Image (cartoon, rainbow, N blue to C red; front, side):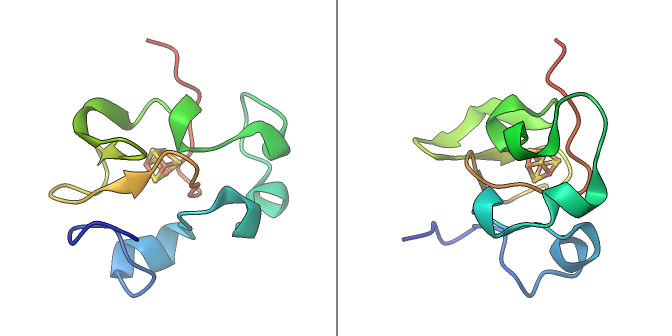
Length: 83
Ligand code: SF4
């Protein structure tokens, strides 16, 4: 079950970025964002994932202030976690 502050499918920014909390139900292949082959991309390996926000599988994303994403999710702003 998602936390009360999870990013939802109805969030305008989530719609614009094609977020899904389950990357296997995402359009990561179509987007072909650079840095890793698309099938390998999810929030856990994204630069915008905030490891010190949230709990368990529900973590922060810098792009979604006040909310939580799932580490197994994806959106079109996916960017390799480089530091
Ligand atoms: S920017 Fe990165 S951490 Fe945030 S929802 Fe998109 S893929 Fe997940």
